[PDB]
Amino acid sequence: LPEAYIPNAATEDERYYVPFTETVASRPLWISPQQNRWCDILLAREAGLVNRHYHPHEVFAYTISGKWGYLEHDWTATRGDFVYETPGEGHTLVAFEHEEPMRVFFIVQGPLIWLDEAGNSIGHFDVHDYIAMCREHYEKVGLGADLVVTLFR
Amino acid sequence: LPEAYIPNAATEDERYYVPFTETVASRPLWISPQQNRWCDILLAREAGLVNRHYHPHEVFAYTISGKWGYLEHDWTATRGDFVYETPGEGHTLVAFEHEEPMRVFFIVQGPLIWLDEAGNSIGHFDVHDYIAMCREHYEKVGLGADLVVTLFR
Ligand SMILES: [Fe+3]
Ligand SMILES: [Fe+3]
Image (cartoon, rainbow over all chains, first blue to last red; front, side, top):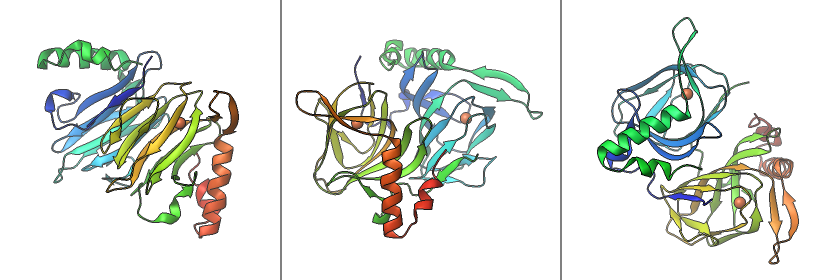
């Protein structure tokens, strides 16, 4: 099957970004239903928060714009910064209001498992959940659910 | 073991870039000797070429600056463009002379296997080769070989 080339990944066209939390949205770029893995541009136009969760596997990121981090580490990432998260580490992603929106290229190995404050597992978000959310949004905004399927490898 | 945070990944400080071919160099960001996998910033300040090779596994890229591509595909990538290469596909990477240097964030699963024109396998470049090259360079330019070891996960 073919390579993928997606020009202007962190596009200014808002239709391509699928709401994930109230303050954070994602543009899918590449999705592997068999590997439970995907690549996306994560976007927060203002202050943003993704609730605590862990990944059984690794996460890689390259910061395109803005200012973000995880509360469980001591740094904050701005344009040009690289991040790797170790498997199994629980983390809470935050985005700060900056001149530019937070835009981050992420390569994610799922599932995410949502954690309450006690550190107990309360829900999950896996590649099928991601596909379903992206197809539903893309159909609604007029891009078509079939566009999401074109991303699959 | 810890997360990795590398600020200013595609740095202007030339010491961090390790010569790979005559025209192309790489800054290691993250290296997994056990997974035969690494992440880097690939840099070409002028015209550049990486000889034909294939990867038994996948490659992901996010274009930071410049203009580059693989001769075996019909596109060329510029700032902001995402690329995925399918496992087992033989490809020849080129960089064009542009206002900015070619800078690309790559997540590579090794080995690379070098190909002659007949499509026969003539050499290889694996994670141990990469570590050895990076340690040798970093020692020479004064960053220290031990810095490379700090990248390992
Ligand atoms: Fe996460
Ligand atoms: Fe390659």
